[PDB]
Image (cartoon, rainbow, N blue to C red; front, side):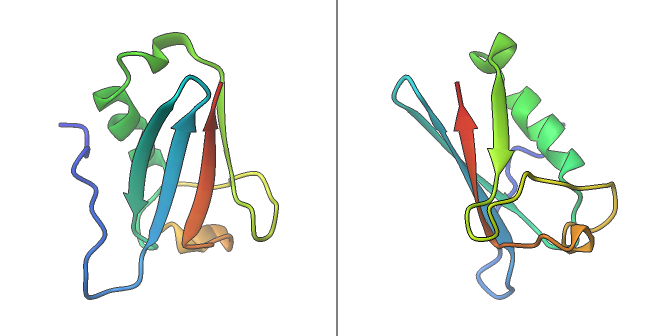
Length: 89
């Protein structure tokens, strides 16, 4: 089952990415530093009813860099910003 319930524990430091829609839509995504952004694929697929065919992108603001994962933990990307911004257009 797509993660979907990816929630940030209230006892450990984890990264949380939020996504807003240019049409007045908003979604919250919480990820763990030891997880792989690949998990987002199942999560998105779970709530991918409208995104079905929407051009979107995910990027962080602090360092101002384009997302970049791999497959292992999330911090391994060296970009663990904790709070990232995702745009939907």
